[PDB]
Image (spheres, rainbow, N blue to C red):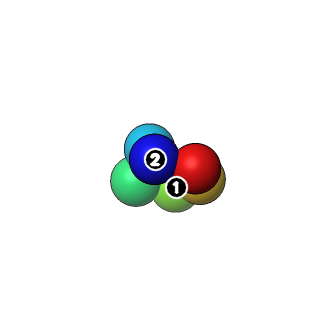
C-alpha cells in the first residue's frame, strides 16, 4: 500500500 511496501 505504501509506495515501498504494501
Name the residue tied to disc 2.
1
Q: Nearer the viewer, mark 2 or mark 1?
A: 2
Position of residue 1 relative to residue 4, above or below, is: above
Asked whether 1 or 3 is in front, the reply is 1
SS of the residue under disc 2:
loop
Q: Is residue 3 left or right of residue 5?
A: left
Which residue is depicted at the point 58% across and 50% down? 6
Which residue is depicted at the point 59% across and 53% down? 5
Q: Compute the Cα span from label 2 to label 1.
A: 8 Å
- Please count the marks in the image: 2
Which residue is depicted at the point 44% across and 44% down? 2
SS of the residue under disc 1:
loop
Q: Is residue 4 left or right of residue 3?
A: right
The single residue placed furthest to the top in the displayed view is: 2
Q: Evaluate if marks 2 and 1 touch, with contact meaning CB atoms under 8 Å apart.
A: no
Q: Which mark is residue 4?
A: 1
The single residue placed furthest to the bottom in the displayed view is: 4
Q: Residues within 10 Å of mark 2 (few under 14, many from 20)?
A: few
The single residue placed furthest to the left in the displayed view is: 3
Residue 4 image offset from top left, x and y in percent:
52, 55
Q: Residues within 10 Å of mark 1 (few under 14, many from 20)?
A: few
Amino acid at each position: 500500500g505504501s509506495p515501498l511496501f504494501d
